[PDB]
Image (cartoon, rainbow, N blue to C red; front, side, top):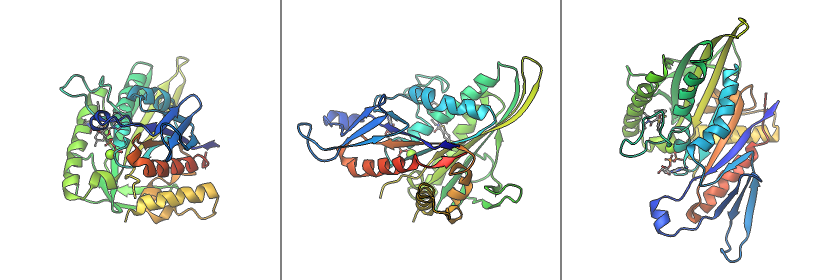
Length: 331
Ligand SMILES: Nc1ncnc2c1ncn2[C@@H]1O[C@H](COP(=O)(O)OP(=O)(O)O)[C@@H](O)[C@H]1O
Ligand SMILES: CCN(CC)C(=O)c1c(NC(=O)c2cccs2)sc2c1C[C@H](C)CC2
Ligand SMILES: [Mg+2]
């Protein structure tokens, strides 16, 4: 057994909000694992709504804080031969993509491997090599990026095929939580010095999918997957063979047509209510990620929220959803 761990990350105010002397309606207390939301009142007299999570990260949280506290422990587990998934869930504009992918610091100040704005995916890839290269491990790394837009499936990493070619999926008859995606490419990442270019290619494929599909970056779900095959020779000369898997899933924005997002919510409702039928089959996303939801994968949710009063209602909606999720048992 193990419950799904759910963490909240509040994003900071941006330029416009900061010059507009915006006041945060959100207070985060990481030590009591608590986010408090100002639901009407004033900064003078106020009703507040409070929520407890597995972790909360306030507006001051940096990319390094998330990597150290959330990602390292999960990566260690994938290195031990486990499957793990991290979802980012939240309204458009609250930092899902920032969290999972990150941005470049302006004016070329950093290399990619040192950029403070690097998110979970590049930091993860960089550390896999940095951990396994030096200790005595023979290992391979494959990555894939399967994205879902309007219940069709796209491979965003494959450098020799166009983005507009949809893929097909079927059930795996060997394993039962399982599906085969015909024609999804697993790209072998030979060393840390091939990481950037692989991701750059996918970036370029993203730009075009965006031209072709309306509000692609908001309405699409992406699943970036890393697989590590490892033959470890222990200092005692014993040879340990293991398979680690990590899914990094950047969900469609949750703001109030998206069958996968609808079904995700229904799948979570079913799992926390222990309704005996769980509607996995009702969308591509919940079929692909069936094992992440009441399955054998260690699963974490980062719910991204905003400090601004404008987003009160959607912030509340994110936190209620995220808060339900805590009750789901995986193994
Ligand atoms: N923790 C953060 N620190 C700095 N900027 C952030 C943070 N979270 C989100 N942002 C900023 O907010 C804007 C939108 O974030 P983005 O990753 O596109 O959100 P989403 O993917 O949820 O729609 C971007 O300008 C991004 O740089
Ligand atoms: C900054 C442009 N890049 C990196 C090429 C990204 O947008 C990006 C990622 N970010 C990054 O790799 C970085 C940010 C800052 C330092 S490294 S991770 C990722 C992509 C795109 C790809 C489709 C899937 C996974
Ligand atoms: Mg985004």
